[PDB]
Amino acid sequence: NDELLGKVVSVVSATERTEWYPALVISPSCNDDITVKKDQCLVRSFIDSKFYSIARKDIKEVDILNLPESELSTKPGLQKASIFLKTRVVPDNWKMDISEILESSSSKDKEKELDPEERDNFLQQLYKFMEDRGTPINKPPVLGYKDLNLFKLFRLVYHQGGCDNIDSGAVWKQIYMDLGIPILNSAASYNVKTAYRKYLYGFEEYCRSANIQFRTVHHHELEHHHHHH
Image (cartoon, rainbow, N blue to C red; front, side, top):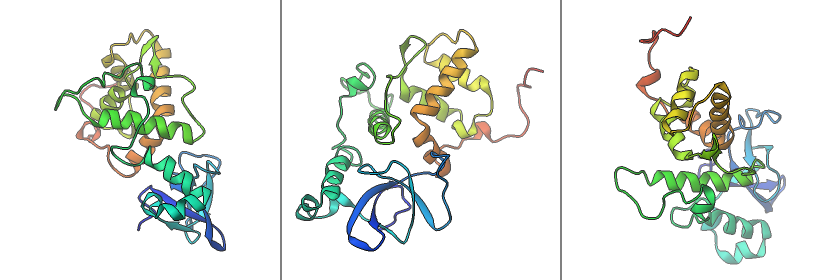
């Protein structure tokens, strides 16, 4: 059923396929202390361990919410999975207050074409996933004393080719500037880099590793603007 998609999988209790605990296949680049070996995968258990390295032999991928509720409800790990997943891995079913996420997030009613529905989805997914990885939103997206439109920064960076494609501090500056937040000084360059790197690092890592973010912007050798030296 493909574990490697970065979805929820069953991590069994080594021998018991009966009792297992679901986890999410994630990038081991999110965890510096755990490191992945070729036979193992990096899974985040929403129910138990936030980062653990387990061999793919002990991992049987499954769509937890696809399984019968009688099965789920009898095994707490499977049940909570059903609960946890329905609110963060399925399209319509993603629900958290979009206004708690930013402020209001302008999700009142939508502008087609001009506004990407992906924004709301992304904010929602990131907020859910932020909490379950042990690096939750302890501070809301505000940057430079004002509301930080998280998806704008994502879109902006993505428009620069992606953060994997960002080599210049000028870009972090430019993305921060596009939000309309006063760049002030280099501390704000720090701010924006920190923001993207803590809030979006998971999706970033996955996005850049699975080749989603990649544009001609960073497909060059020489620059048109020689860097200040």
